[PDB]
Length: 37
Length: 233
Length: 312
Length: 40
Image 1 (cartoon, rainbow over the protein chains, first blue to last red):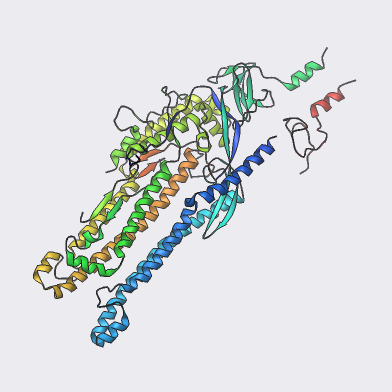
Image 2 (image 1 turned 90 degrees about the vertical axis):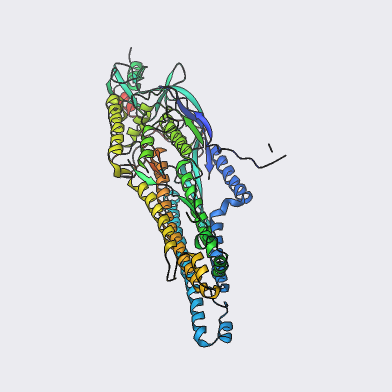
């Protein structure tokens, strides 16, 4: 929409995720999801 | 303990599969492209009969009726060369597509054997996530696999340590990881948070208190020693 | 090190410009040969789309671009040779820079890839960051941060070795890993035949293009290979057969080129499927398959971007 | 290979009312049994 027109752009590879790495602070999941693909 | 929840999640995912297939038209794109490529190959092969290939006409009867046998021979020879080149191109393209389909079918049979007939630990081979099981589905000139995967969710942060030192000895987890909620230390699974009291039955002794880098000081409860302290005046 | 070709050079051929150029009579005669030019164009477009899809399936396996923490301490393991170097303009690692340095027109157009080398290097850096910060969790679901000494301890547990062996010999293991990473650069910088697969692919494509161009100089039984020359020296009725045989020769050359390109594209597609499988099973996890992620008990693998390929 | 169900072969999780289809059966404890021999 930017009235809508064709726009050109540099493609994004994805959102940046800065993993909170440290000498400690393990990340453990408390739940789960049953996914069918 | 969470059987009903997992069953409901599986039922909801199976129900959403039908919606993701009935709504999205590009779900069967591979099979549709195979069918369309075969149809286009056949249509091109049958339309190449209308090409003259430098001859006076594409009809053999017209060439035979209009021209004398001497030059009709070379006209028919040009037509034969053109149609034979068309047939050879069609057969070569069919061989290439058949090799591609053979590779795809070998992959499909491998995935059937390793996901439906068993449980595979190959990452991203039987779906995205920890593969539980797969269900095959018959498709026109193809096959559809319903990969049931285990996806972790709702992760929390816990202070961890490689080992613990209680009586000058380093204790390492047999199965799990040492975690801390801030004040107390527990042992839990790596893929699911289930805090357990660190005991001798959950850990093993190796080395001393000074060899491990990052070791922490925490008590290791011994059930055998605790039971002996109960039967003592 | 393991090197696998992932993509080829996407080539587009203008059949009319190649067979005829600017001659109108040649084009009118080529119109009588059917839809061979359409088939050739469709096959080349399919090959290009297939190369793009192979690159995407090999490198674009993560949904998020994971970043390394500002502190590069991972328990003594030095990843500076594989992590992206922000000093140089291209955000590539020293090993990736060495790999990039080691790898070196009548209607023929070369199409540029969809993903640039910078985007492929960014995908590789995201894979490396996810592997060094979360291990194998980012491949199955959300990225779960884990200390690298503990990650390597769990990977030691996957090969039948207790984690105490690693926790008691952590400095030795780190020194051995650093020495091996250092020797990898020497093995790649000194030996020129290490990257022979990608160079062979590039040379095969270039030689096919050069042969297709040189086929225009052939007469194919005609009196000359120049269309204007035979147009100016012969009458339209008698130059017709010369134009026809030149068109036949050039069309056979184009068909041979397209068939060879299809065969090489099938080979490169198989190689790219193998590369994506090895990525998923060695970088995103620990594989039990013998000799699939290197010689020995596989602990972990690190991808490296290469021109038209990938290095593990 | 039928083995005697003891504490060394099983682990405890949850209570007696969370599992669907759970059966009531004795779980022998070697430590408790050996402590009964050394008792008046």
